[PDB]
Image 1 (tube, rainbow, N blue to C red):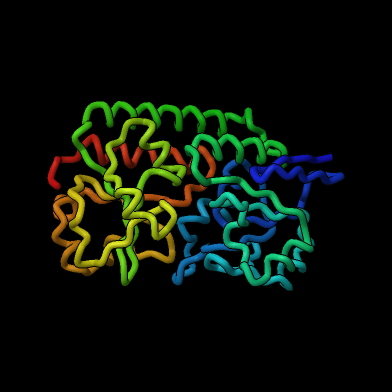
Image 2: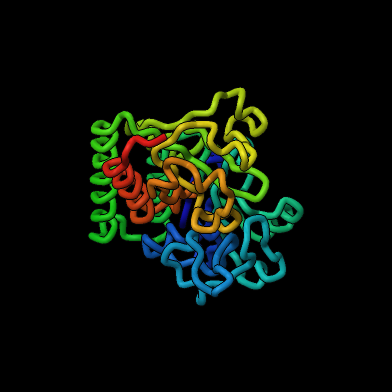
Amino acid sequence: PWSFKDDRGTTVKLDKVPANIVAFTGVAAALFDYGVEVKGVFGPTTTKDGKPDVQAGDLDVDKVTVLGNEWGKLNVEKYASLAPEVLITTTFDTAGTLWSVPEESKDKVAKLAPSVAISVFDRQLTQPLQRMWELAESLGADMKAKKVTDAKAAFDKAAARLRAAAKAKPEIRVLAGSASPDLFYVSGTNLSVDLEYFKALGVNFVEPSEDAKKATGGWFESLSWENVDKYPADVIIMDDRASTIQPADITEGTWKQLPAVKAGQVIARSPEPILSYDKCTPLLDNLAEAIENAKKVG
């Protein structure tokens, strides 16, 4: 028998370990790094060139059945066809809302299999990493596999590296942004698993006021493109997801004139980390590297 109590406090119990798992693409990507296969995914999975999306990690995107290829899309008839035994996703709120399960069909989806949510709300990254590790082991992973303990050691090494970098370079101000056509969004550290952890390790973030973030309940501040120079920043970390405009493609003149952009001090941020140590290690290394080499320019 298999049992797991998720971050909504609900305990799913099945008579056997589920063989037919369906997961949000980023959760399937994490389980893949622990050698747990899924049968179906939903979420940003492939790009228009047919390549794996960043949230698909190392998943074999040809083998799995893609039920939806963007956030909030999940075809229920095709989901039923997988004979699903559990659905697994993340959750970003107090309510335990299942991330990316279409609101208009979530009840239909829930009829066909129990769900497991891993919370990525209002906590540090190490939390959901260890919760996802426990889930993967319950599903048949070997958590004492050298691939996995090496991964955890590499993550701990990269976390010490970011702590050291932030101690060496306390003057380097990091801005977390996400680009869309109407607005550039500046995140605060509070509420995000990655940013809360990077902050705990000593990174100096630009922090919009709580007043400036209240239109999103404290997640981020919306700025017009002409006002992206509001906060002086030395390193900018930009949202990497499918729905957002990547830094190479931002054509707006105010952006191109940013001290950080002119200095080449822009890297990716993954606001939806794939919850494996393997895939979170680069998030620490990349930010450490940027801080280690950054010039104060903002």
